[PDB]
Image (tube, rainbow, N blue to C red):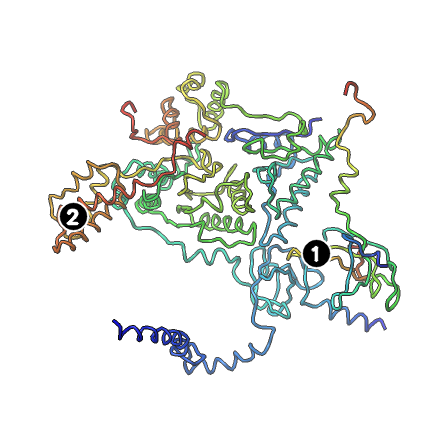
Amino acid sequence: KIKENSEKIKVNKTLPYLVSNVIELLDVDPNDQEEDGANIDLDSQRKGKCAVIKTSTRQTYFLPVIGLVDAEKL
Amino acid sequence: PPKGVLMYGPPGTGKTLLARACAAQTKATFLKLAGPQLVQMFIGDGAKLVRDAFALAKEKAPSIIFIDELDAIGTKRFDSEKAGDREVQRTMLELLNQLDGFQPNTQVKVIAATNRVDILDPALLRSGRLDRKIEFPMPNEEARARIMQIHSRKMNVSPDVNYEELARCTDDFNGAQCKAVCVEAGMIALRRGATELTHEDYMEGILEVQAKKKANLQYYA
Amino acid sequence: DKSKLKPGTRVALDMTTLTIMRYLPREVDPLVYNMSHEDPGNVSYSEIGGL
Amino acid sequence: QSTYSRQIKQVEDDIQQLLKKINELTGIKESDTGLAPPALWDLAADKQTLQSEQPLQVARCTKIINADSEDPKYIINVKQFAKFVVDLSDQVAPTDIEEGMRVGVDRNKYQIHIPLPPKIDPTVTMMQVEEKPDVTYSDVGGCKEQIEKLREVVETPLLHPERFVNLGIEPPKGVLLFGPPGTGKTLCARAVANRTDACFIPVIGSELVQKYVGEGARMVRELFEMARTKKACLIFFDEIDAIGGARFDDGAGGDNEVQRTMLELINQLDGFDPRGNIKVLMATNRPDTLDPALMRPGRLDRKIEFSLPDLEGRTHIFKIHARSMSVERDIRFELLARLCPNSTGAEIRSVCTEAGMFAIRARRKIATEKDFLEAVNKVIKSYAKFSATPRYMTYN
């Protein structure tokens, strides 16, 4: 199971991908008040912690951060 | 302690030299910086770059941050630039709010030079948020005599120049203008086959440096 | 809830189907947070006589 | 009258339909140009068409810092205003991607084939730039007082820099040029340069107005760096009443780009500056908008008020043009010069042009004395008209 996960992140990690800057964190709770799919997790169909980034187009995204390197680590 | 010093008035007295001299005495790190100047390519990417610079300069205390051309950062006006300038502008106000204490006041010093005093942050003008704010008046009699003396040390001291006498002749020449004058005085001297700067040499240098030109309209000139 | 939408609050919506995945708690601008905490004074907040 | 009138109505309908046909008339064929050897070329082109990895986009690295667990990435920014990371399809190195360096990256891999020269700004500006001048005093409107004053700045420190260094002075290199258009301010600067035997490069601030906000400062900075590289040269800044000119702190216009450019320019000059016989001239073509920061004495050593050619200087330059074309010699040009107010060298040459033309109208092939009279009347009046009420300005 581990080798299979490990190869998929890497295919994601290779270019193309956007670069932006992190203006602020929020780190809000896991599982807000909802139930949908999968399992309660840091991010999934259920996402807790996120960091808001101001990208270079003058667009803003608040997105959930992968747990390989957490939003708390961000 | 005093939170900092503000310099305003017509420049040319040596507002950059002054800042540099004080900072040298103290052996505090000297940032010559101006708010929106690190904006590279786009406004998005450039907002970040300029904000980061502002913060960086404040830190590494003790320090002296020298802000040049703060007319733009000041936003006395009802319009803003809304690019990188906004960010640097907000962080300054927050910073001044935080500074009142005994402890940050000494550590972080700020010195600023701007052309006017009415295009600085609306807060700065409210109260003395920096202790002792100095206006530089038009050149007094003592000022003139001194700007000549320091320059004669730089080149050479002739028996001919007399600072007291020189001050009377001329009116309204500041430090920068004066440096140009001493360089000019030297030009005259090189023509003569001299190294000495004569009293006549300093005088003549004064006329070339201004708007005035040889072969004047007037029939007494 | 239908109370997780009210004018001005943050929401996360899915990109491909524009339905509400979750509630996103509103950002707090750091600038407002500085204004709340800081007191620009260094003088008494009880009284100043004759004022 | 009557018979024609019907032909008029019909012809209009004809012309309408014809306007569409010109497109076809030029060619139905989809082609532009093509010779038998681009057929060979075409096979190669096909693959490049096929693949979406090519064409190569132009991007520019604003700063080098990234190299996060792969051979150096950096932040390269494409002109769709989005940032991307680089990989190798040639190489990547600290030196292949730099602070200014532009890059060629793919649309759907974002890997570097080749880096491109640093910045867009120095390649385009190169065409605009002319080299060493070959012009002389007679051509400016003769020997003028303003000419001699340029000699003092340019000729003396350049030819013999050793005297100023020993004495204890730094040498003067700066001049502020101001006055009305047509005086020959660049022409004069160039004139002195040629005799002195030093390079000249024109820089026009208006010619580069590539913006994305704050971008304008990076161009100012580059033009300065290039001048500095060439020792024993003069740099003349034309059209810097904007982008590197007057601030607007009273504004309500959404500008900050002129202010941004100004900020960088003052700062580079002020305190010290690394020069070695690079003369800095500034020409301000606008009395209305002026930049005080630059304008006052200091690092930029003198101010000279640029004035129109004196009476001997204009007579002398006219003489030179006059002999070349057909003129009657004993010429009444002297009587007219003295009668009239100050007249520039540009103005006198137009006299010669206009006098020729009156002469053709009369049906002579010699431009006579009468013809020169009409030509001076015309020129003096046209120059004279412009106002911007100077007293109003003096008051405030």
Quarter-wise, where is residue B73 in the image? Answer: top right
The amino acid on which the numbered mark 1 sits, given as a three-letter code, is Thr
The residue wearing badge 1 is A60
Q: Is residue B132 above or below residue C14?
A: above
Which of the image's four quarters has the N terminus of chain A?
bottom right
Q: Residue at x 55, y 52 (%)?
A: D215
Which of the image's four quarters has the C terminus of chain A?
bottom right
Q: In this rendering, would A18 be left or right of D375?
A: right
Q: Residue at x 59, y 77 (%)?
A: D51
Q: Position of residue D74 (x, y in %)?
A: 64, 59
- Label 1 to label 2, Cα distance in Å? 72 Å
Q: Is residue B26 visible?
A: yes
Q: Is residue D333 above or below residue D215?
A: above
Q: In this rendering, would D287 be left or right of B60?
A: left
Q: Is residue D245 above or below residue B11?
A: below
The residue wearing badge 2 is D371
Chain on which label 1 sits = A
Q: Position of residue B72 (x, y in %)?
A: 58, 40
Q: Nearer the viewer, mark 1 or mark 2?
A: 2
